[PDB]
Amino acid sequence: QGHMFFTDWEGPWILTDFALELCMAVFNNARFFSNLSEYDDYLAYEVRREGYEAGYTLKLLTPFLAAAGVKNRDVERIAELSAKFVPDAEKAMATLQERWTPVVISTSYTQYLRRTASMIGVRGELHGTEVDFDSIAVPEGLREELLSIIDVIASLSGEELFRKLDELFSRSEVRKIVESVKAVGAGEKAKIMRGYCESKGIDFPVVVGDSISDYKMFEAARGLGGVAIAFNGNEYALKHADVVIISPTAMSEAKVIELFMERKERAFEVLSAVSIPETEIYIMENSDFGEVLEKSKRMRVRLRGLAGELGGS
Ligand SMILES: [Mg+2]
Image (cartoon, rainbow, N blue to C red; front, top):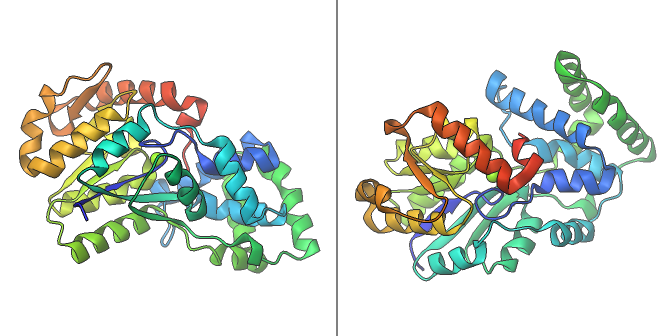
């Protein structure tokens, strides 16, 4: 197989925020989701709660979805309905797969990754949060408790919200369900990527991401002497990236990934020669952070809309 590169899914390839889309399809409650996702950002990056990883939002959402009666077929259907790709995603992936193998590492459910990856002909390795809804038992009382508390959580903010969620997720019966999920958060992405570098003898890991959930994978790549690439990243991603791509087309990713896969350390010297419409590529150690951030966030929202400002994945 062609040499491997590593990539997040939502942002680089698909525009969908699947955790959000599930929440909206099942509960139609954006404030509930924003609150859970803010909590995730808070615990993972601000507090750095021991054992907590950025992108565990979907893990936290799982007991609510189970309580609402979500089954694996529903996950697949919502995956189908909500799938919206970065412009040129399939065209760019087809170009890359002529020579290289993607390893996709996502916080979203592996089932959803499988269904959506096939839509743009991904032929690589897929890693995500693992759940089997059709096995999760939720007693009638607990179902009532979880469904009732949604409006409560949505109504809270700040310290009171975080306090309430700490309490909720510490309940033995809720914790039970949360622990049945094998989640992918920031730490797991780093571990998965390192495992491939070891097993496949990759001296120069090329990793692509866009949010907090990618930051440990970014640092791990940097430590190993590879490169961390953000595609329309947010502040969290940019604070840990070597290279930032600001672009409305996945063809910019195809080109930059190609350059690094071919030339490794010597790709840096040719990035300024890449000329793709509406595409800017910044080497962060030679750039003004604030300038790059403002531009990146603008493109981020252009492509992903309001979902492009959410944390949690
Ligand atoms: Mg992402």
